[PDB]
Length: 496
Ligand SMILES: *[C@@H]1O[C@H](CO)[C@@H](O)[C@H](O)[C@H]1NC(C)=O
Ligand SMILES: *[C@@H]1O[C@H](CO)[C@@H](O)[C@H](O)[C@H]1NC(C)=O
Ligand SMILES: [Ca+2]
Ligand SMILES: [Cu+2]
Ligand SMILES: [Cu+2]
Ligand SMILES: [Cu+2]
Ligand SMILES: [Cu+2]
Image 1 (cartoon, rainbow, N blue to C red):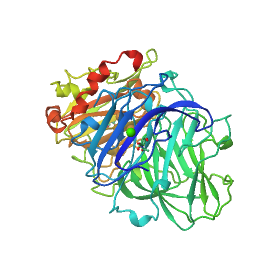
Image 2 (tube, rainbow, N blue to C red):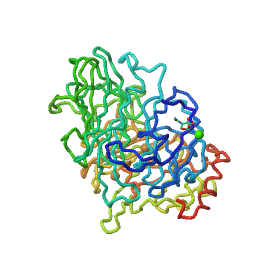
Image 3 (cartoon, helix red, strand yellow):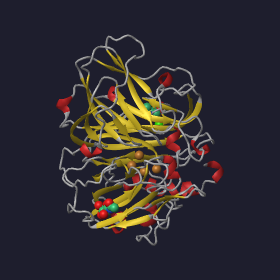
Image 4 (cartoon, rainbow, N blue to C red):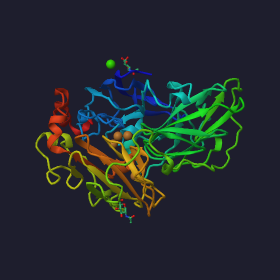
């Protein structure tokens, strides 16, 4: 693990996490990237060094700190052409920000095109010295991080129209169907001990149905936010979501299968794919022979309730927010592009933040045309995103904010009293009307998009220009940020 001041080298490396050798885009030569840790209230100074050289994937880069609000530091949020131009090959950029009011489980990833699929993704944990759930567990450290990743054998820019993952990597290890039987990830526990496992989806696409043979899971945290403990026997986790769950190692000393079943790709466990191993101290060095019992108590988002200040903002009636926005999704089979209310997001040449700093303060004047929505400050926003467009279920992610999910997928019931509070939500399927609320307490241009990276690349996104009149003042960027676009725009396309 590394601390909140760190020097991250982004470079290409040949790796074989599932036994197939491919060039990747990695942080300090590992997949996943190193765990970044901090304590509540810390200041981050993450110096990102771009040493990329391999022209089969993108060689510029930009890193997003997923789930961190970036109040007053919108310029450090990371989404390319929304809050910055990319860091050019050979150049560096210091992400300098603070987290005064957040503690929980997060992650970081490239936010340039589909580059994070090529390997630039890792976990980020902000610990709370006064964690209200601390009495529920004994162990919470780097050994209790569980990353779930999809992995591809072809570089991201070579993507088929509908890419499909080759393997599931748990803590960086896993197998592909028909591939070598490489060692699976092992998570070691001591009988009688209680573990805070921090489950991080760093997926580019599949959701995972996560379970551990013979063990219930007590969910205590959702996308960085403390929730009332909820015991389940399986968790369906969508791209970019995080859960902390407490596991009580109260079963016989043995090896137990950890299961992460994707919704796309190989949807079984044959030959140890989509699997890892929970090993009790004293158990043999062997693979499990446990079997899966049918989930009778799967996690339902409708049962998650925030531990602190439960309750959605605004009046507890439908459309009873200050601003009400409905997002209609479509997909063109001929062009392969997604649209939101008729507009496909294409990255603008001038990043949205720079446009605003340059005087573009209206939806009419902000690029890309039709994709940028202005919001007034200190108001309650309600967003509905009905499901149904192809490629689902789409997990939508809002930057700069956590939101309250007043209506979740698979339910027609509204909850304003204690709905789940998180930052990535599945919008479900045709017939769902997933609805979220948040308060505009954070000026800046904030991305809202499907976190399936292939769909984001195909245009499934909008930008909220929240309080554009204040944005320059509240987010005054450092000189290093001013130089990013001049450097980037001087690049010939050959060098990207
Ligand atoms: C990445 O590698 C550089 C080069 O040695 C090192 O200075 C830096 O601290 C590393 N960062 C990590 C391991 O997070
Ligand atoms: C969808 O959700 C919005 C937000 O609560 C609500 O106003 C609208 O009536 C809902 N429509 C349907 C058909 O459920
Ligand atoms: Ca360095
Ligand atoms: Cu993310
Ligand atoms: Cu994010
Ligand atoms: Cu999607
Ligand atoms: Cu994003």
